[PDB]
Length: 89
Image 1: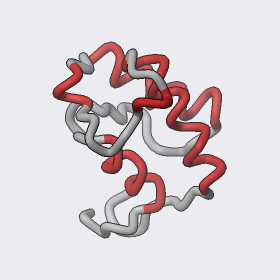
Image 2: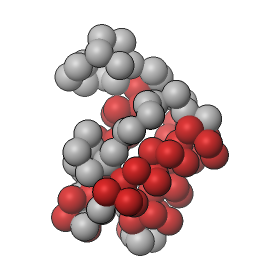
Image 3: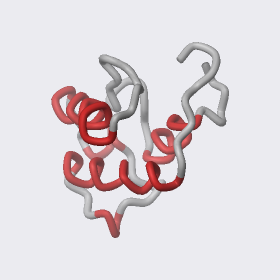
Image 4: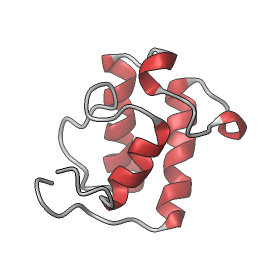
């Protein structure tokens, strides 16, 4: 975070989508990069719960208050974020 990201495998990339599916309400089979967390109405509650599960269920050292409502936008945004291959920050 703030120069250098983390880096997850496609296995962790698979595990995230199901946590997202649950808390977003979008079926895994419909989860495409066209989906937009803000467009779907992902509130503060859900967006916090998702990144929280990342830490507890998956064991991701993402961050303490990582919210998909502000720090992420689309689905791919979360995907790339895991690796940090955008080097946006």
